[PDB]
Image (cartoon, rainbow, N blue to C red; front, side, top):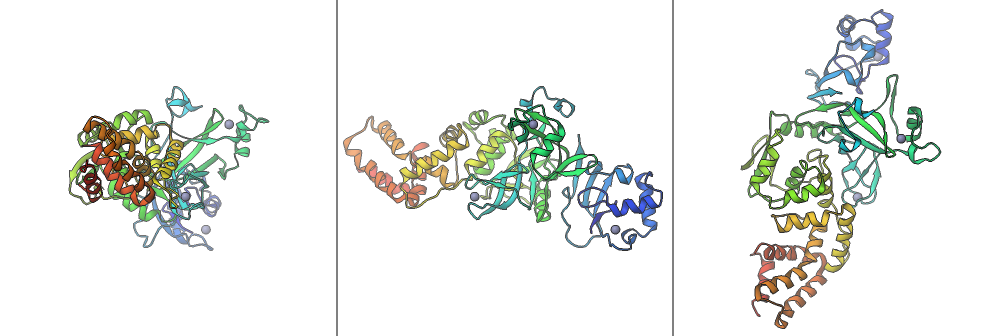
Length: 473
Ligand SMILES: [Zn+2]
Ligand SMILES: [Zn+2]
Ligand SMILES: [Zn+2]
């Protein structure tokens, strides 16, 4: 059984066998340092006659007596210097600074509408698809971004995203929706009805998830509010990764984020990729504000907006060691890019959905694509239109491609109207060609995409064929 260098367990709480040792010795009321000196006299790891409490973690804790040590007393956690091997799961990430804090007793909030909802992610299999990816939600259920379905949380790597100010977690509160109990219930009633597996201690009930320890504050509008009473900080307010496989993931986060300023490095041309779009969304108050923000976006505006927050420095050119290299297309489902803003959640969903393509025409795929996009947000269509037609959008997501590509027949009609002054009968074979191309379904989505960009901001082989047809009239 592995402990830290203060002989507390992997979950941050003291061990029963150590409390019994110190109690028999009459050291229970002593300060932490005196208790540890005693334990060392008993040979530390081998102070128990039935255990070998190998020390895996190095932690710095308050002097508070051992029996009163909790995850809320930790200030620093990292791998123990002489421990050769991989670490077991630990409540906090390694190489992290730990901070600690009805709602008025926690945050300077004027009303619940000023609280921000944290982004909680779990790495797990989606039953609906078979894919394994980072699903976004809370500590009870999460949504699979590929298909939009909800799955119950399972054991695996977990993370909380970048901490917003006044961070809360909003959970469906069955105690309030159950009309027999309703709002104004007692605390005991909430925890008995919620049905989720909390960690019960003499000091209350808490939840350990994604590098934070949450506690219950209160309810509003039949939702329960939890707050990260304790949270890790590995750099730029990121809370790191905990759970199976977290050690490798943390190494990737620490290399990039644990700096005085996080270097955002745009490699090659500045294109509004999925990764850049969500980084900018992180700084937008609302989805509607983001729609206005992305209009006319270029590198300079991106640099100014991102750097204005103080935690980042934006540069461009060649890839650099230790920098946040953006330009090679990487998955947006990661502990990195775990932004908690409203606009960021919409952007993540838009660029992560897939289509159920089965020999369908472009017109059919567009109808399905719009249905998906409308479900995500009523601004999703205006947001995509802005990114595509007032900026320089690039993606390989089929839902976004299907929505835009299906409109090429209307854009072509208007484009030909603008060039030649009206719609001519001689130009019908160009529209008829597109209608036949729509029968290719997925096979034409990339070809149409390039055509839309060509006419949108007015040469690839798909456009050379189309353009040659137009030049016949
Ligand atoms: Zn023991
Ligand atoms: Zn899925
Ligand atoms: Zn409630």
